[PDB]
Image: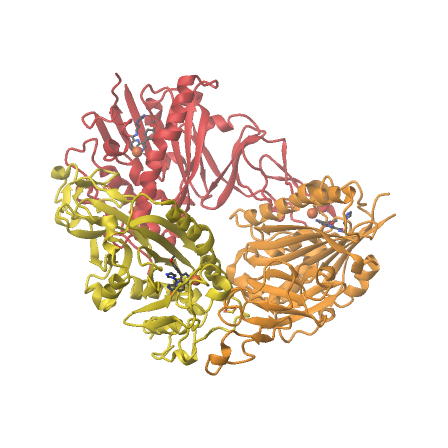
Chain colours: A yellow, B orange, C red
């Protein structure tokens, strides 16, 4: 039996509850979200700086797919499943500059940076060798809002159709997105469903108790969480200890988050690549405009690494454990207040209302 | 198809065999035993001393359930599923002294030590906020025989209904139970079905060959294993005569009162899955500060005695999956019911068999 | 629906493709290969040198079965499931010289080295104790080509029926096989289907790119892969500044007689599940006291040669689960059947295919 949700699930944030627990734990729900959501949506994978020059490539894994994204010699950005068409060896590893051809490690077939088979060894002596159908298998990729998105659906349109208006507002909050460079990346296999991790991001109800260092840097009467078109913006004014330093927190469907902290001069990005119902690989990327980091930046990197990020990781991990309990009645009340203050949870209701549309 | 046993399974200990091997390995058998037995029986979790003072609390995990047991400000012992009613964060960790209210770490809802929602931050501004229906979810707990039992079955009666006479007999074996204090705990995730570990305890057929260091005290002809009602007693006199008690109680807690009757060890089996059982091996002394002779005995249990029994049940769990294991094992019951008779296994499995009709 | 193949699957190596990817990943396909192939075929486990003397024994694990192969008092080689018939404890571990009877470590039942029950403690006072049928459970074992093969099918015939002509030809490749002794064993749990590891051994298409240090001996001009009857031979001439043999035998044991013909390496594959295969990589020399050249070569295999092949099969296992991998891979057979032809794969897979009708 398949679990289904109503169309109006969390349609009313003022009186709303989180998903029945099975949606956070069921492997069958995950397998449905994997193909209905993560194989048919634009999945953000990197900032443009990782792929800015010809021959630049990166590799990612999401929902079990090892994918390579590569800027071809023609400067055309492409993405491919990272698997040789001869006998399935992976083609590239890590990140870097590709040679002028991709040489598979197992039998040294070569491919052009557009996936075309360049040379199959001993090809000429193999009967009825299919040169056309021995090329790398592509998927869609789009450079959007200064970042890179992939899509496994061959019939997808463009990122703007998925996140209407998002590219312009993000560039409004940070005017140096195009000069950012990856300063630090935190990689964690998190034992929480991807939806639990989004829930946590979508509210600051927990900042008082769970985030001491991120609690004075934020005004509760000067904090607004507005929903948009498959994304939301959490905006507020800071004063930890520019007559009004602002901060931005974007959530975009399905689960990528873009943060522009006070100053608007750098970004952190949360990438969620789901693994299974109770596992989500996370990239926590910190981006600065300078390549050689000052020590105030290196300290900031370690503060997120060792103090700030561990707090949210424990939260989502404990929640994943708790909601399997028979002592958890099943659903959790979303603490929306009618003024949408800085500790209102209504943003969770907006996210989950979108998720619910995939469970009819 | 679900496995089942004749209700007369091991009804005759003189001619009996262990479960067909699938009962030790099948996930569908385990999931049935998990709910039919471990979610509906009294599960011993601690000695009372761990919960003797107001605000004292402990946490246990059993059959996938994180449970908190907590002595309220009002001195009333209660138990709760260890999960906040708002959005599922765990409430307490480890063991110790709870504050006067429980503060959930995620959104800082407050709960009185009886589970009551005290204050949910900003509730007053949340439409249609439910007062209780947002309280901690409790489960039954009872102090019995000086120990603490929990029960996830809301319609369970009392521990005495489950173990008729056990409190009476254990208090005759050790008269200082309430003065006991936890001296040491061995936590082991053991890769054996919980029933393999009970099988192991229910017989001394193996003590000669498998426990060399535990042979210089026991007497083979002054050893008796008598069955009662959902518990059994292994009773004997030890080489000088000091007596000793080995209680097994349904489903899988064992209480040992070694010679001297002044201390106890207790085996708690918290099953995890068909082939995994969390074990607490607790040693309890009446004194707070351990002597160095007590630390040595603790060490012997930890490094010599317990490894022998853990190795046996781990090896058996592997071996009974072999296609070369014909399926069932003969229970070595003798007419005399000697110090090495295995008939106690038949009593244990006959009760288990009643849950597989 | 269960996955099936045409009988002519890879019957024509000139126009052939590897299995549809489900055959390398499906646990149902594995369970069928497990029982149709690995429980009914002769499985090579060791060289004779390990079991040459009375009471010598080894232990192996393959397809979930812990097996002991033991040379009886009477110099008769036997194989048994390594599980006591009483209550399932394992009987022996590792390799070594067994004592005149096997004494189980749980209840000290004794067995003779031919599997018969010697003495079951207290049996005399146990009602209806079955002495015949309280035996170690045997399985078939055969010494062939200087090696030892087991078979879980008690109606199995002999290894020659499985590998017709193999011993004859192997003894021509290495004339001192009976003089070999185990110098080194690399045990690796490999996350690849057993068939992926065979596919890899069956071709030298990959030696140029994947084995740089192994490239001066791999000459396409002087390298032949001929198929026979459930085994194949990759024979070539090496370049110094001498011939070499590489036998694959059904289902998955590979015997290498490298240049010089004075030593052997052997690849034993013991599949675990669809995506896990335990491998033994055995290096055999005739002398017991290794020289530094031999000690250096063992480490070259351990740190240089074998890691390259292990990475190849591990990446392939990952890659063929990709939705970007079209079902099957083209087997690169060339008309000449050169040293880089992949036709050996088609021979192997056509045989496998016979078990998937
Ligand atoms: C170092 O960057 C990060 C990265 C992640 C976050 C972050 C962490 N945890 C929970 C959260 C909930 C909500 C939000 C949000 O609504 N977004 C912005 C608010 C936080 N902000 C401060 C300055 N700029 C943004 N962020 C959260 C903050 C800072
Ligand atoms: C001290 O804690 C343990 C913990 C585990 C055991 C234990 C382990 N395995 C099998 C067993 C069979 C029978 C019995 C028994 O008769 N138990 C009663 C007191 C035995 N006693 C004598 C001297 N010291 C202790 N115990 C067994 C004993 C003792
Ligand atoms: C020395 O032991 C090993 C052990 C493993 C191999 C080996 C490993 N991987 C792929 C392979 C493909 C083909 C062949 C072959 O052609 N095998 C025949 C013996 C050729 N020879 C070379 C050096 N010495 C002997 N071997 C492969 C070779 C040698
Ligand atoms: S896998 Fe054979 S060439 Fe890439
Ligand atoms: S989860 Fe306990 S307060 Fe929100
Ligand atoms: S288990 Fe081997 S003798 Fe009892
Ligand atoms: Fe947070
Ligand atoms: Fe014991
Ligand atoms: Fe190789």
Residue at image location 23% in from the left, 68% down from the top: A165
Quarter-wise, where is residue A340 in the image? bottom left
The reply to whether residue A332 is visible in this rendering is: yes
Report the number of numbered marks. 0
- Residue B69 in percent (x, y) is at 65, 65
- Residue C348 in percent (x, y) is at 29, 41
Viewer-closest of B225 and A6 = A6
User: Which residue is farthest right?
Assistant: B241
The reply to whether residue A81 is visible in this rendering is: no
Residue at image location 53% in from the left, 67% down from the top: A325
User: Which residue is farthest front?
Assistant: A243
Residue at image location 41% in from the left, 74% down from the top: A341
- Residue C215 in percent (x, y) is at 25, 27
User: Which residue is farthest bottom?
Assistant: B128
Q: Quadrant of ligand 6?
A: top right
Residue at image location 39% in from the left, 71% down from the top: A222
* Quarter containing the C terminus of chain B: bottom right
Viewer-closest of B212 and B348 = B212
Viewer-closest of C287 and C191 = C191
In the figure, is residue C64 to the left or right of B6?
left
């Amino acid at each position: 039996a398949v679990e289904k949700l109503p169309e109006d699930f969390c349609a009313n944030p003022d009186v709303a509850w989180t998903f029945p627990k099975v949606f956070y734990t069921s492997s069958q729900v995950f397998e449905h979200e994997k193909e209905a959501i993560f194989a048919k949506s634009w999945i953000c994978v990197a900032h443009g700086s990782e792929l800015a020059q010809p021959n630049d490539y990166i590799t990612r894994k999401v929902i079990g797919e090892n994918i390579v994204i590569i800027r071809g010699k023609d400067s055309v950005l492409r993405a491919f499943y990272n698997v040789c068409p001869h006998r399935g060896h992976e083609l590239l590893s890590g990140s870097g500059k590709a040679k002028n051809v991709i040489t598979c490690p197992y039998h040294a077939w070569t491919f052009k940076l557009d996936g075309s088979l360049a040379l199959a060894r001993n090809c000429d002596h193999v009967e009825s060798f299919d040169k056309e159908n021995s090329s790398m298998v592509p998927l869609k990729v789009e450079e959007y809002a200064g970042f890179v998105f992939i899509n496994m659906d061959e019939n997808a349109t463009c990122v703007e159709d998925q996140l209407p208006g998002f590219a312009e507002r993000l560039n409004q909050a940070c005017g140096v997105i195009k000069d950012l460079k990856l300063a630090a990346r935190f990689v964690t296999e998190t034992p929480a469903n991807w939806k639990v991790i989004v829930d946590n991001y979508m509210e600051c109800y927990h900042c008082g108790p769970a985030h001491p260092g991120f609690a004075d840097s934020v005004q509760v009467d000067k904090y607004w969480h507005t929903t948009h078109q498959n994304w939301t913006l959490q905006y507020g004014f800071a004063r930890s200890s520019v007559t009004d330093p602002e901060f931005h927190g974007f959530w975009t469907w399905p689960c990528t988050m873009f943060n522009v902290p006070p100053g608007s001069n750098f970004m952190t990005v949360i990438y969620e690549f789901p693994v299974d119902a109770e596992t989500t690989l996370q990239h926590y990327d910190i981006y600065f405009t300078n390549e050689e980091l000052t020590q105030d930046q290196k300290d900031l990197i370690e503060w997120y690494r060792n103090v700030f990020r561990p707090e949210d990781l424990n939260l989502v991990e404990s929640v994943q454990r708790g909601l399997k309990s028979r002592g958890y009645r099943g659903q959790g009340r979303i603490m929306t207040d009618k003024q949408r203050s800085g500790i209102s949870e209504h943003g969770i209701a907006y996210f989950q209302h979108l998720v619910a549309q995939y469970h009819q």
